[PDB]
Length: 188
Length: 188
Ligand SMILES: *[C@@H](CC(=O)OCC)[C@H](C[C@@H]1CCNC1=O)NC(=O)[C@H](Cc1ccccc1)NC(=O)[C@@H](NC(=O)OCC1c2ccccc2-c2ccccc21)[C@@H](C)OC(C)(C)C
Ligand SMILES: *[C@@H](CC(=O)OCC)[C@H](C[C@@H]1CCNC1=O)NC(=O)[C@H](Cc1ccccc1)NC(=O)[C@@H](NC(=O)OCC1c2ccccc2-c2ccccc21)[C@@H](C)OC(C)(C)C
Image (tube, rainbow over all chains, first blue to last red):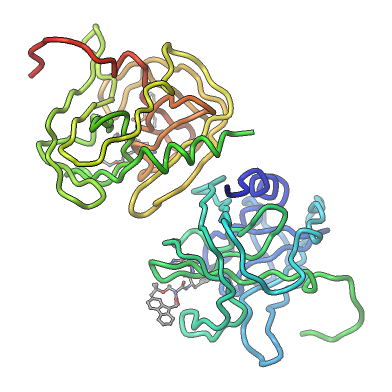
């Protein structure tokens, strides 16, 4: 069966409601004060987190070496609470998955779970006019309001929901190497 | 934890999408060709079931001995498929419950699960101007589109979602005695 228990533990301890100029998004906290949000959320220098205005200390819109959108933006937030470190639940590599759950945490849906079935390493997607890479696909009619939703299997947090076409849903991959402690680089 | 596995088994085998003049509702099939739907769905002599026009052979809008709305309408449908008999999962008596799940099956949400936490035997509710009895209440911000949604705990199907006020959700109780094989009574 789908790993509902795992999805619930991730949602309970590692999600907040984020709100930008573009609306509300489920937001996955990954470690310390670092979280993710879809790039098309258009994060600025402040953001609402559970309706509390919060400084965005850093925001990195990920792109691959072809200079193509990956649709993940990693943010560092000025908050007191640390997120439980869930980096060990992130996949090392691209993969396909079975019996995944999509989990949403917004004002409208504070806690909701959708089994999306098989998830395929899809690759290239034209997302609302933006070429995008490293997309995961599931055959489920996902809707507006579900962006940022966390895609899991038991023991793995594999991506965040970013798009759909009325029949299929698409998530941006999360990989373990996106969040490893590193060194010195001018990035803005 | 919440009984997601049980909720999923009920949804998989015992729900259809019903559509009346008032819109779409999750519809729980109980046994044979007998199902339930909230009375405010305004069931007529035909109904759409998974988008297929279907004759409604009988419809009984339940009321208690005070002649007050219970908000459950039991329907008998002209379909080929029988529903798996789930009467043994229906509670005998009114009760309070822990860690319930609300499960929705509509066109917009073909499969969605919401843990609603504690469910209380609430009693009287004024439902959109209609006095209504035998209501179950949960502290969860349920929304339009969730009516008919099935409320479960492990091993019990306890009600169907009928209402909310933005902070709380309300279900009409299901009791085992609503569906027992009986005898001869002019009811229309
Ligand atoms: C989540 C964010 C949101 O609700 O918007 C607020 C600004 C939302 C989820 C999806 C909406 C529809 N169902 C969903 O699962 N994502 C988007 O709207 C996303 C942009 C975005 C905005 C903000 C944050 C993150 C993302 N855009 C779309 O999902 C877009 N879909 C899309 O481009 O799909 C690709 C299609 C494609 C590729 C190749 C050949 C043919 C097609 C095709 C045909 C028909 C439809 C889509 C595609 C949505 C907005 O596009 C449609 C046309 C479905 C409305
Ligand atoms: C499901 C059916 C649907 O979507 O409508 C299509 C016709 C829907 C679910 C609920 C909507 C809001 N959140 C939900 O969970 N149910 C209804 O709309 C239901 C009527 C119905 C129509 C068709 C089938 C089955 C049912 N009506 C309401 O839910 C109504 N809520 C309500 O009456 O709550 C009682 C309130 C009460 C009692 C005593 C003191 C104070 C109050 C109070 C204060 C403020 C709000 C409600 C109540 C909705 C429609 O009413 C509001 C005002 C929330 C819009």
